[PDB]
Image (cartoon, rainbow over all chains, first blue to last red; front, side, top):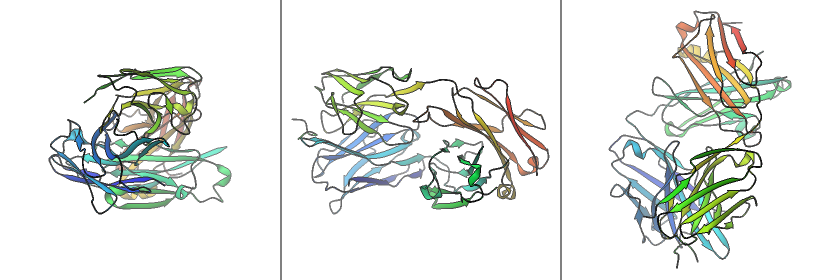
Length: 215
Length: 6
Length: 213
């Protein structure tokens, strides 16, 4: 089917440059256009740029005019956005987006977004610690501590365990590094038979940790 | 008329 | 370009209530308005297009109306799964502009939290730091107080909280409070306890453990 995959996010120093790409699958970019839409943390959606399938009809929002450059690969089904002179206000999740309307109905698709962090800090992979179930139902979890920048994705048993999972929003510590915990409630009947592993992914630092949680 | 419609 | 003005900014209502959200365009957009729903941590989803038509899969309780400059999104029967932020959008031309968004919260009955305490892991103690986590699970309303006691000494400046968004089915919250100390300062005291007060609890519930048992 249709999928849009953004890549290129991570930390970038203020005043420096960063290149985003969006790979489009399940359709040919031979009609209509492609959009970039960004969302600052806790803020609203903001359309940023558009490009047509043939490179024409390029428009930018006033907030990024003269700094962002949208373009498409003439050889592949991929669109790019070069982002120069980045400032703190540019920190946002950046979504690749495609929308049009036919007699068949609406065609509206979004990537999962990539987080650009405009910061003077360095990238740091996290450490993963188990929240062991101790002395009805029992709760266990994983503490993902001291990482920068966001985000960190956490799953349990490679996504086979979802019910009762609470992965809390990250918290900015005194050190300036992020930390979060993901917890899950299970019946204490299963602590002796079922294995519980949290899968932690920090893409900006190429960190993939599988941590088994034991009583 | 609309560039996103038909 | 065309400016979109959305209201209200935030609203809370009960299950089954009618929710009304309005958008204004700075100039005529005919009926080229769409309404998007975005839930916590996920990408936006198209709900309404051409002011009034529903995207595939959208429940019938979502409706839209309006033309030219004034448009309205209506949820005829607010459900816990509708807790999200909603955005209007015009698509008259090649670009887009969104409204500021309306966060929709839901009201429900009081639910007391289940409190769990987690001692610091031994691998973190080998790393040189110590974190004590206290978990408040599936409660309403959001307002709660978590007090950290170390040998019955109240703490301040060394704990941080995080709260999930309302659950998509029962609309409760869950909260985590993390007491972060140095390994040297942790191996000092004996008893670590988190005291929790909440409207659903008759008296403050305390979860405690002794260091190294």
